[PDB]
Image: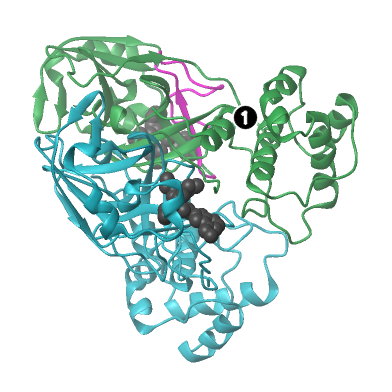
Chain colours: A cyan, B green
Amino acid sequence: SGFRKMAFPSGKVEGCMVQVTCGTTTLNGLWLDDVVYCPRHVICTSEDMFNPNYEDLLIRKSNHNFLVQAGNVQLRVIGHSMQNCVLKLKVDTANPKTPKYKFVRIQPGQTFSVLACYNGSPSGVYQCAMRPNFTIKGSFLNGSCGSVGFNIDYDCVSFCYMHHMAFPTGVHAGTDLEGNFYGPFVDRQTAQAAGTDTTITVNVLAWLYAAVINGDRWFLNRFTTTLNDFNLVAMKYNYEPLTQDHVDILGPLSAQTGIAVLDMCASLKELLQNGMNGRTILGSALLEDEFTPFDVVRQCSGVTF
Amino acid sequence: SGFRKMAFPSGKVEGCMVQVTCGTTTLNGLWLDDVVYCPRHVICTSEDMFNPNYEDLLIRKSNHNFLVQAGNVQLRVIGHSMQNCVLKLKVDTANPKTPKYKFVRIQPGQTFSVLACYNGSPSGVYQCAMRPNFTIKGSFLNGSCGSVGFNIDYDCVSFCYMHHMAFPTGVHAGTDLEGNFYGPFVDRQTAQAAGTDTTITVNVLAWLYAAVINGDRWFLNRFTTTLNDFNLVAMKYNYEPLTQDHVDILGPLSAQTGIAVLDMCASLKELLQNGMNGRTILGSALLEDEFTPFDVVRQCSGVTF
Ligand SMILES: *[C@H](O)[C@H](C[C@H](C)C(=O)NC)NC(=O)[C@H](CC1CC1)NC(=O)c1cc2c(OC)cccc2[nH]1
Ligand SMILES: *[C@H](O)[C@H](C[C@H](C)C(=O)NC)NC(=O)[C@H](CC1CC1)NC(=O)c1cc2c(OC)cccc2[nH]1
């Protein structure tokens, strides 16, 4: 009953957040076993940001130049190394609150929860989608770098995002936990254009299925379409093409609700061509594309962790 | 940079969630010190729901009739008592993860985070507002009763909501943790009309201030209004009257942005009378009223817990 943008419970990730200070810069790190993972630009100065030689800057630094605090406890650094755009700080204490975890590189269209942190301390949690242009629309202030994004599956935390930078228009960019950026961005203060974003078609369809499950049906029309004729309209409206793999992924939702995927497409096609005409869908006046099919099923069947 | 509906980190509340079983019914409870708090209708049968004598039903029950599980650990019940619509189960073990906490009865217009739980296990977290008609728009399935809503202030969890029931239209109702319902509802399966809801004016104004802080200014007009002429338009549009206490509460936001509260009102008045004309505000096509002034300041100044 009801449908909300829902984040994963954040307690397993809260117990892993730490503060990392090198010189004047303080940001957040992720403490798993005896390793702290943080963005490498913590070793930069204000004037290094425009073109840092990260490898050279790291030469200057010794283990003791890294202050790592977990709450009020200082963690002794005993090894440091770079992996892509992330720093790995080996510490002499293993995090006793380490959950079962994996590092995963997510694909565009997938969603995850963000635990926004400042000074090693969690501020809030919200749900984000990795946009087709490899950005995310989050809420991050100065000092938020090192905040992570994650999914939970029973007991396993799958970390998929670490925050590195913000751009004009509330656009945020980051890396996986192996340090590789999503999309063509660098941890450098230079002109960096995010590509044009598009709407995640399969997530819109998922959210329409969620509307029917929850009672909204005014938009269900009397038509059907082929896959090809739908992707002609999607491209005109800056929607991702719908692939057969997407059709298969909506399968279980189609079976629950009795609406074949291509009938939902016909209903979507008319929403894009005529608009909503003042009406709302699940309390929204815009088509929502930040729910995956799996997000819908979770919320609607009550999957716990 | 960016603005999102943001929940509090839920880890302090996760460590308090337990499963309570009496007979066939299982729901969630909140374990603080040596006490478990849960909705009293856990002692009901399917046919008792229409008109339960809760006091009489509780006579039948003994301490051992209550199964309380925290994860895989069974907690021994050693005392039971009713307080309004909540049950208090004294247990022989004190929750070692009890945070600093208070029980608070919130006022309409205030927001809080909900930790939706099933079988004592957290499923997700999201942010809700207590509507003027004393309902909330959440996402709750069968088995969600006992899930709680809360705010966090530095280290203190202020519990303000416990979930008891759902009504047609994704409308949800519950109690404070002293067991008293918000609004005129009873824990009975009978016809129960929620009053007409209205829009929380002061939260809309807060969210407009958040838009200006974040860069959206197209809606700022060249006009001002008095308090009285604004409340004439608000009432026509099902908006709560704006009180001087609300004007004072928006004070700090007005000072940050340089927009006097009554100028924002003039800008709001024109949005209500002409609509948005296809435009969006902070990525929304509807005026949003589930951010308090304090929610805006938190998100925009980076308050941590
Ligand atoms: C890390 O705390 C910080 C997070 C930012 C502040 C956030 O989410 N809101 C501010 N990251 C940060 O400042 C980046 C620095 C490391 C990558 C080197 N830089 C930026 O985020 C940044 C650079 C630019 C820019 O360069 C030109 C133009 C416009 C905006 C911008 N933002
Ligand atoms: C507790 O798990 C459960 C939560 C519900 C199911 C939820 O959030 N989605 C289902 N609470 C529950 O079922 C309530 C029982 C205790 C108060 C006695 N009852 C209802 O929620 C309820 C009663 C009615 C009704 O009576 C007439 C008409 C329409 C809807 C309704 N819902």
Q: Is residue B188 visible?
A: yes
Q: Give the range drawn in magenta.
A: B169-191
Ligand 2 lies in which image quarter? top left
User: Picture coordinates of residue A61 (x, y %)?
Assistant: 23, 46
Q: Can residue A139 be seen in this view?
A: no
Side of A223 where A35 appears, left or right:
left
User: Picture coordinates of residue A259 (x, y %)?
Assistant: 44, 73
Task: Kindly identify the residue that appears in the image at 35 percent across and 45 percent down.
Answer: A147
Chain of the residue that carries numbered disc 1 in the rendered image: B
Side of B32 where B213 appears, left or right:
right
Side of B182 where A104 appears, left or right:
left
Side of B245 where B119 appears, left or right:
left
Which residue is labeled 1 in the image?
Answer: B293
User: Quadrant of the rendered structure where residue A260 is?
Assistant: bottom left
User: Quadrant of the rendered structure where residue A223 is?
Assistant: bottom right
- In this view, A26 is above or below B30: below
Residue type beneath disc 1:
Pro
Task: Kindly identify the residue that appears in the image at 27 percent across and 58 percent down.
Answer: A56
Bin the neighbour count of mark 1 within 10 Å (Cα to Cα): few under 14, some 14-19, many 20 and up.
many
Q: Does the magenta stretch include residue A224?
A: no
Task: Kindly identify the residue that appears in the image at 23 percent across and 31 percent down.
Answer: A70
- In this view, B78 is above or below A46: above
